[PDB]
Image (spheres, rainbow, N blue to C red):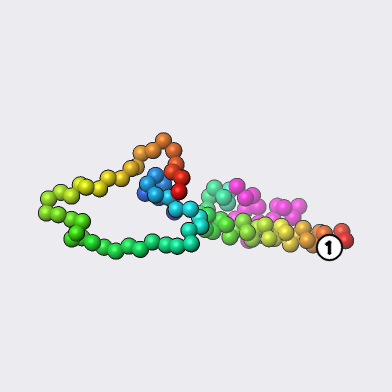
């Protein structure tokens, strides 16, 4: 897949022999005030090797 | 002239398929193209034999 996270943050190769596991958590990762404890990279000089 | 055959692919050229489609289906398309080319080569080899 080609996108934003898959391009410069975490790229997956053609062969993986596996998959991902995801779930929704709107309580532990969210606080009453602003929760700005996570950062991600979108600018890069070139592509990211997997 | 058998090299200019689509063999079920979008085009007879391989770089366009490599740089256009996603690798999960591009690998299948290249596999089909190269196995068609191998079948044609085997037919030519049998005729030469």
B18 left or right, relative to A18: right
Residue to which mark 1 is pinned: B46
**At which x and y percent is residue A37?**
22, 47
Q: Main secondary structure of the magenta part?
A: loop
Which is more toward the observer, A29 or B11? A29
Question: Residue shown at 54%/59% (left/top)?
Answer: B25
Which is more toward the observer, B7 or A43? A43
Q: Residue furthest left?
A: A32
**At which x and y percent is residue A7?**
41, 46
- Residue B12 is inside the magenta segment: yes
Question: Residue shown at 56%/56% (left/top)?
Answer: B26
Q: Is residue B26 visible?
A: yes
**At which x and y percent is residue A39?**
27, 45
Q: How many marks?
A: 1
Mark 1 burial class by Cα count in 10 Å: few <14, some 14-19, many 20+: few
A43 left or right, relative to B29: left
Q: What are the residue bounds of the magenta stretch?
A: B1-15
B48 left or right, relative to B30: right
Q: Quadrant of the N terminus of chain A?
A: bottom left
Question: Residue shown at 23%/61% (left/top)?
Answer: A25
Tell me the quarter of the picture where residue B45 sits: bottom right
Q: Is residue A3 visible?
A: no
Which is more toward the observer, B46 or B9? B46
Chain for numbered disc 1: B
């Amino acid at each position: 897949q080609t996108g934003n996270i898959a391009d410069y943050n975490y790229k997956l190769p053609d062969d993986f022999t596996g998959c991902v596991i995801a779930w929704n958590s709107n309580k532990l990762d969210s606080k009453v005030s602003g929760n700005y404890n996570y950062l991600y990279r979108l600018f890069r000089k070139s592509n990211l090797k997997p | 002239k058998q090299l200019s055959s689509k063999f079920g692919a979008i085009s007879s050229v391989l770089n366009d398929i490599f740089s256009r489609l996603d690798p999960p289906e591009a690998e299948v398309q290249i596999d089909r193209l190269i196995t068609g080319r191998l079948q044609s080569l085997q037919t030519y080899v049998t005729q030469q034999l």
